Length: 83
Length: 83
Image 1: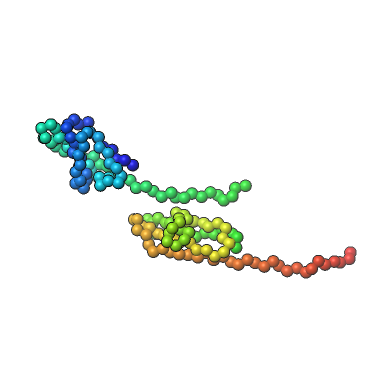
Image 2 (image 1 turned 90 degrees about the vertical axis):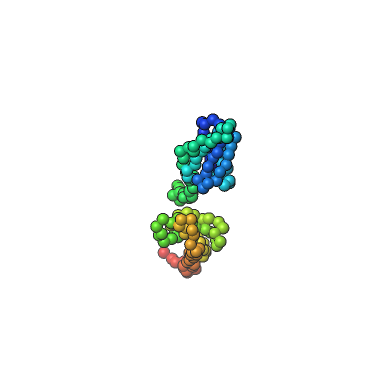
């Protein structure tokens, strides 16, 4: 599933930091992560905001993300031929 | 010959099981530890894979032996008696 992150904070650009240190930016308050990219990471994510002067806010309190695995089917049976 | 039978894996704590219809685990048969097989008419084989924490063990092949068909019993030719 797509991983979606957002902030209510206002700024000129946003810095998003992945649990393993990967560092990307967006022009808006909403970021999405494609399951096939290097950012599809579970764990603690943080954000900082860049204003027009190029000054960067203290990082946010991390938000944990949990990416769950997909279980097996536990293939079901029946009770044999039924009269 | 002609009836149903069970297969039976040993028990490994925490393991998932998977049975496959052929070697090379190309086609999955079931996910049960003790699945059944319907309509066995001749000898066949099944392949068991056991997986723990995502790591499979060596594929375990088994054979279900099918007893051979029985002969018709033998009775005498049409006979005839008087009252």
